[PDB]
């Protein structure tokens, strides 16, 4: 097999020689965040893999809740396991929200630079957010509310000015060797101002969703779960040689 989703017998083809690792957001998991994007990439011939991270005992389905440094270590082990199995030298990473930000910890402090070619962030909180902003996720994930507080570490670590965010962004945003893409939406209600999602460096491409389609009004959750315009742009970043401009026509 040269395509699949969590199929560890998958072997990346010559057209798509790097396997893709998908990294969910806050309150997400390896399956539900990626019900549209994973098949979408499988149909374009990628070997796709998705991990669970930040699990809290007694809270199935809703992850990204444990300490984000520990989450980055889970990502570390998971990428090694995907590379050990596929044979490939490097993986490409796609992440939504927390999952677009957390891999920068792996890249910067756990030697992920070696093992990663590209990091694509969809609505990533790259310089953190507020607890108030994170509460705007709750209507999409009701039932998680009773198991969390302001001290839930996966939430507190995302707060702009936290010890975690301070450590992560003390130096520059990027690490040499890696191609970074950020896809943001101006209607983001969770991570504001939305420009703080953007990365800075020589090898960064920041993209505003509404530049691609002016009438795509996706907010924070939609952009990383169901938005095919966003996902077309993800497919461009994963294979820049065969990229084609993303317009409203990608909505199907
Ligand atoms: Zn499910
Ligand atoms: Zn899970
Ligand atoms: Zn390692
Ligand atoms: Zn920065």
Image (spheres, grey):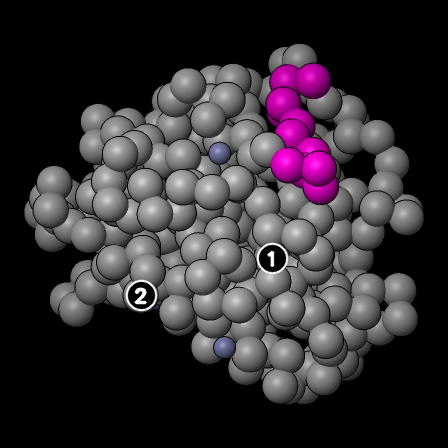
The boundaries of the magenta stretch are: 201-211
Residue 202 lies in the magenta stretch: yes
Per the rendering, the mark at residue 50 is none
Residue at 44% in and 55% down: 105
Residue 240 lies in the magenta stretch: no
Q: Is residue 175 above or below residue 70?
A: above
Say which residue label 2 marks.
70
* Residue 65 pos. (x, y %): 25, 55
- Residue 134 in the figure: left or right of residue 152: right
- Residue 163 in the figure: left or right of residue 183: left
Q: Is residue 56 above or below residue 204?
A: below
Say which residue label 1 marks.
93
Out of 13 and 192, give the one closest to the viewer: 192
* Residue 122 pos. (x, y %): 55, 39
Q: Are circles 1 and 2 on residues that touch, CB within 8 Å? A: no
* Residue 159 pos. (x, y %): 26, 36
Out of 66 and 136, give the one closest to the viewer: 66
- Tell which circle, 1 or 2, labels the residue nearer the N-terminal end: 2
Based on the displayed image, in which of its 4 quarters is residue 184 positioned? top right
Q: Quadrant of the N terminus?
A: bottom right
Residue at 19% in and 52% down: 153
């Amino acid at each position: 097999t040269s395509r699949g989703w969590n199929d560890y017998s998958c072997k990346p083809s010559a057209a798509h020689p790097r396997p893709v690792v998908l990294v969910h957001g806050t309150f997400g998991n390896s399956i539900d965040n990626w019900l549209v994007l994973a098949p979408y990439l499988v149909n374009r011939g990628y070997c796709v893999f998705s991990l669970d991270y930040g699990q809290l005992p007694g809270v199935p389905f809703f992850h990204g809740l444990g300490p984000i440094d520990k989450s980055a270590e889970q990502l570390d082990v998971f990428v090694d396991k995907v590379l050990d199995a596929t044979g490939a030298p490097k993986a490409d990473l796609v992440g939504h929200s927390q999952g677009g930000m957390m891999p920068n910890y792996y890249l910067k402090f756990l030697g992920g630079a070696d093992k990663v070619n590209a990091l694509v962030g969809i609505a990533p909180d790259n310089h953190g957010t507020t607890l108030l902003g994170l509460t705007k996720l709750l209507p999409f994930f009701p039932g998680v509310e009773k198991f969390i507080s302001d001290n839930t570490p996966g939430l507190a670590d995302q707060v702009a000015g936290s010890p975690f965010i301070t450590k992560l962004t003390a130096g520059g945003d990027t690490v040499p060797g890696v191609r970074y893409t950020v896809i943001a939406t101006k209607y983001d209600q969770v991570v504001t101002p939305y420009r703080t999602q953007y990365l800075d460096g020589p090898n960064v491409r920041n993209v505003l969703l509404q530049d691609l389609c002016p009438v795509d009004l996706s907010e924070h959750v939609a952009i990383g779960t169901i938005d095919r315009i966003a996902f077309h742009e993800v497919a461009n970043a994963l294979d820049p040689a065969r990229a084609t401009p993303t317009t409203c026509a990608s909505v199907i």
